[PDB]
Image (cartoon, rainbow, N blue to C red):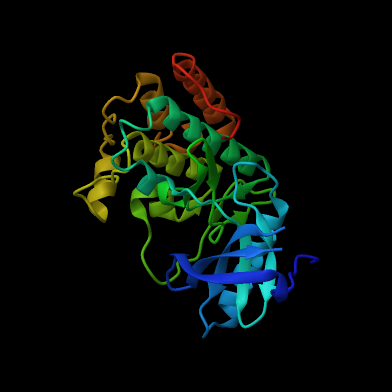
Length: 282
């Protein structure tokens, strides 16, 4: 619990990166002066919400990976605040919109590959993210992606899954595996399903999943043995991969150990056909 920071080393700018009911995420700097994102709990917060962020803060402290937003520490001042590294690029989906001629598929597969490495790591640490989606993948730059928002993250321990309570609000159904909707059961393979939707979102350059559907309109679809089409120009090997990520039976769905290895091959294949180059994570 040496994770507390000095309010004085933190300058919070009047810049909001995102928001929501929990409060807002703002940009600032922390002492040289590293850029940081600050999750500030709403002013009128409650024990429950303060405990959650506190648990969230605790989970992030256990994670040490390049493809995951790092926790700088927690700061208790005029409000409870989660201070974590900054990913200036922003969300993967808003980033890819209208950029099919700027960001080739090889670059998209690069970012998706990095995400698969982060999740492989998460799986090993037996943590379930639950909210993996393009909007929660943040870019440091165009060749460096990071998984963020561990607000719904949870440790599994010896268990390979858990049944969650139902909190007020709506569920991002289009990103949930069948067993998540029918039995509220979550696991790594559940994150794999979300990873598959994430691949689709990215490979389709920012489009919304099941665009035109909503609610039980989606589950009925999946139930019948149907899924999203192959995005335009997405290589067969990639689609075969995201498709396998949508295997109904939990037991028959690949784990991140296999997804990463498969995503790695699909990526290096494309990358080996590109002209020019960039650097490591840059």
